[PDB]
Image 1: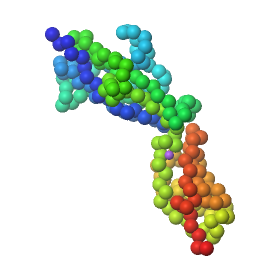
Image 2: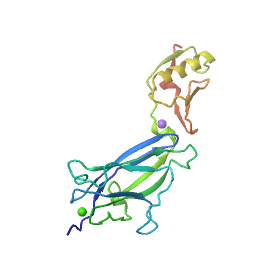
Image 3: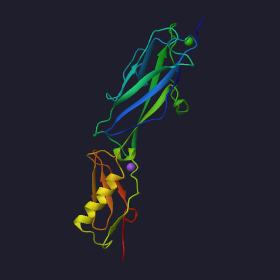
Length: 205
Ligand SMILES: [Ca+2]
Ligand code: NA
């Protein structure tokens, strides 16, 4: 007499080359119980569990127990992995995937191929370049002798000030500064952010 499938809440799952990610989806059922969770590509029919890319992993604690999937304490599925440096992106790449859960009566969440289900049982995994994860602080001011001709010492000073203001940028990202004070941050995936000189340097001319 339970003919209602488990309901899923996911999110906007943005991930970044060279970075780990972790998201948690939430699942409830009217019976209070969920016995199985699969995350999958749309194709392949009812028995398919195929999911790509292969670096997308998931796990669900406490399956198959009474009351493991209620509104007050939803079942949670960890969706996680490590994005390779060699993923192809433009600004981004999209992968649309589905979370299917089963209750004890065998009712399974239905896959509906429509963007108006995104954030429920359907989610978009958006892969972005590494630069997009970081918003470099354009706080810091380095006084130089002449804004049109920074010395090596002045360029190193600017780079050190940018690093000190940005502890969360990847340690192995490379901060370089040109002879006019323009800052380039080159991330491990070789994408870049740039900071115009007038946000980091001044002179007294
Ligand atoms: Ca149900
Ligand atoms: Na950025």
